Length: 162
Ligand SMILES: [Cl-]
Image 1 (cartoon, rainbow, N blue to C red):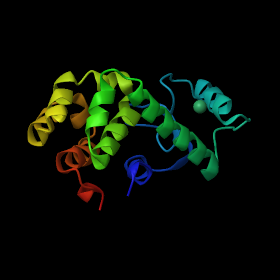
Image 2: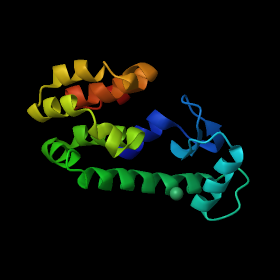
Image 3: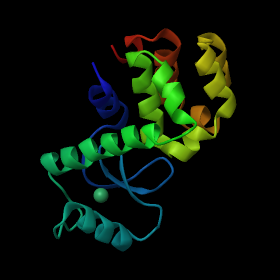
Image 4: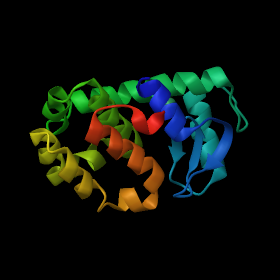
């Protein structure tokens, strides 16, 4: 099991534009198009991203390319984040995945603003960071997913995904 497997599951796969839970144009494996409410606008960005005239739909492979880049970008954003790095650098492998999953979902910045839960993760105080992350808009907006992620951080295992 690894980050790729993890997020594919957490995000699913769509070949067609779709709207998320926040109601945003999205595609593939949680690949955010635009926050704007113009399907057109979303079509353009999709085109720009795929590099061809898509007319709203991509292929699996296309989806997969966006995804690999999306995971790469998340990794680099972590490594480049002054708040994120050390955290990341201090966790074992399962947990870095979890850190990566959240960054994928909210952005360096977003994730970087959980400064209290970050310390805790730093102290390796699983149980409490966990309680802490739960008091998040994030946890209530999408509790099941949020729970897997948080369990993964807590335990440092993949049980939530098996
Ligand atoms: Cl792109």
